[PDB]
Amino acid sequence: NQIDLNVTCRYAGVFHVEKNGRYSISRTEAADLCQAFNSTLPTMDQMKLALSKGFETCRYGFIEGNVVIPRIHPNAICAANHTGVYILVTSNTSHYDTYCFNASAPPEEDCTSVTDLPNSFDGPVTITIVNRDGTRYSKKGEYRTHQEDI
Ligand SMILES: CC(C)NC(=O)N(C)[C@@H]1CCS(=O)(=O)C1
């Protein structure tokens, strides 16, 4: 019973979380997952400020109200070569990665590693935070409050 959560640098408190190395998070699960990091789904304004500080990914993820990819450098295989906060318009499917926003993080680029999952609750799952540099933090718990996400 294990879940891997790959996380990034934070930019103005905004970071990306990928579950189990594939697009696998529902919108309800995303809100619960950010809550386990004492975080919330970013607003569009918070994501645009993060982009301006250097944030970009090549993966779709939830924010409040939309599914997006922040892009700085045009790349043909990331958001169809667009720059800015690219918004997903048409998709058949419901599961993506997520973005989270931690208001207590540093104001600009914070590329230190994540070493805690502070607000997870008691549960049976081994949850492992995987940083881009490979460093890991694991703890037994749960963060999903909706049965359909388990
Ligand atoms: C170039 C990017 C996609 N590579 C990347 O993120 N990785 C190789 C991951 C670092 C930690 S891991 O989760 O074990 C695999």
Image: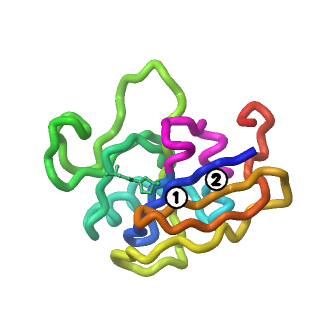
Picture quarter with the C terminus: top right
In front of the other: 82 or 44? 82
Q: Does the magenta segment cover residue 144?
A: no
**The residue tagged with tag 2: helix, strand or loop?**
helix
Q: In this view, does 115 lie to the left or right of 48?
A: right
Q: How crowded is mark 2: few (under 14 residues within 10 Å), some or many (20 or more)?
A: many
Can you give x and y, in whole percent of width and height, for residue 136 in the image?
Answer: 56, 66
Quickly name the residue at label 1: 100
Q: Which of 87 and 72 is in front in this view?
A: 72
**Figure check: 96 above or below 5:** above
Q: Which of marks 1 and 2 is nearer the N terminus?
A: 2
Give the residue drawn at x 84%, y 54%: 123
- Label 2 belongs to which residue? 33
Q: Nearer the viewer, residue 23 or 130?
A: 130
Q: Residue at x 40, y 67 (%)?
A: 9
Q: Residue furthest top?
A: 92
Q: In this view, does 69 lie to the left or right of 97?
A: left
Q: Does the magenta stretch include residue 31?
A: yes
Task: List x then y, in percent, for residue 108.
Answer: 35, 77
Magenta residues (range):
18-32
10 Å crowding of disc 1: few (<14), some (14-19), many (20+): many
